[PDB]
């Protein structure tokens, strides 16, 4: 950002915006970690 | 706690924790109770199992 | 012999995860990887080791 330069680290993956990482892309990420961590919803 | 001296081991719980609740899953727990013996292999072969 | 099980749970000893418990926590396509560390024990299709 132009505050003089400024460097702010995006700590988690979520600070990447749309057009770089959309919502359904993260939703498919949750689908593949649903398959990959053997997690099942409670009865 | 003798999982290596009993009959019904940990895959039985590991499947049945997350099974759908139909009569078909009761049949799944019925059919994985099929023993592994040579006579069982011949008779499973003989009727196309 | 139902009176000695709260004694077993009274001590805070935790059991390490045995082989047949760490053999179910993998999906079928991750089972053939080197990340599956229980591959050196699965030897016979009839017998467990």
Image (cartoon, helix red, strand yellow):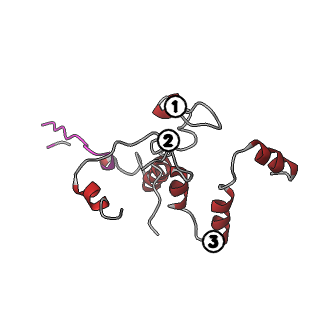
Please, which chain is the residue tagged with disc 2 on?
C
In the displayed structure image, the side of residue C23 where residue C28 appears, left or right = right
Distance of label 1 from label 2 (alpha carbons): 10 Å
**Residue plotted at (82% across, 45% down):** B42
- Label 2, residues with CA under 10 Å away: few <14, some 14-19, many ≥20: some
Q: Which is closer to the viewer, label 1 or label 3?
A: 1
Disc 1, disc 3: CB below 8 Å? no
Q: Position of residue C38 (x, y in %)?
A: 48, 34
Reading the image, the residue beneath label 3 is B22
Instruction: Identify the element where label 1 is drawn.
Output: loop
- Label 3, residues with CA under 10 Å away: few <14, some 14-19, many ≥20: few
**Dot placed on the residue nearer the N-terminal end, 1 or 2:** 2
Asked if badge 1 and badge 2 are on a common chain, one would say yes
Please, which chain is the residue tagged with disc 1 on?
C
Whether residue A8 is in magenta: the answer is yes
Please, which chain is the residue tagged with disc 3 on?
B
> Depth check: C15 or B18 in front?
C15
Instruction: Identify the element where label 2 is drawn.
Output: loop
**Residue plotted at (50% across, 43% down):** B4
Asked if badge 1 and badge 3 are on a common chain, one would say no
> Depth check: C9 or C27 in front?
C9
Disc 2, disc 3: CB below 8 Å? no
Disc 1, disc 2: CB below 8 Å? yes
In the displayed structure image, the side of residue B16 where residue C37 appears, left or right = left
Reading the image, the residue beneath label 2 is C23
Q: Position of residue A37 (x, y in %)?
A: 45, 48
Whether residue C45 is in magenta: the answer is no
Q: Position of residue B39 (x, y in %)?
A: 79, 45
Reading the image, the residue beneath label 1 is C41
Magenta-drawn segment: A3-14
């Amino acid at each position: 950002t132009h505050c003089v330069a400024l460097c702010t680290p995006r700590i988690v993956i979520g600070n990447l915006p749309d057009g770089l990482a959309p919502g359904p892309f993260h939703e498919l990420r949750t689908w593949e970690i649903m398959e990959h961590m053997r997690l099942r919803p409670p009865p | 706690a003798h999982e290596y001296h009993n009959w019904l081991r940990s895959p039985f719980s590991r499947y049945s924790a997350t099974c759908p609740n139909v009569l078909h899953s009761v049949m799944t727990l019925a059919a994985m109770l099929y023993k592994i013996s040579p006579v069982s292999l011949v008779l499973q072969t003989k009727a196309h199992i | 012999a139902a009176r000695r099980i709260p004694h077993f749970y009274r001590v805070r000893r935790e059991v390490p995860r045995t082989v047949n418990e760490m053999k179910q926590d993998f999906v079928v396509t991750d089972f053939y990887k080197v990340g599956n560390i229980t591959l050196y024990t699965e030897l016979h299709p009839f017998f467990d080791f």
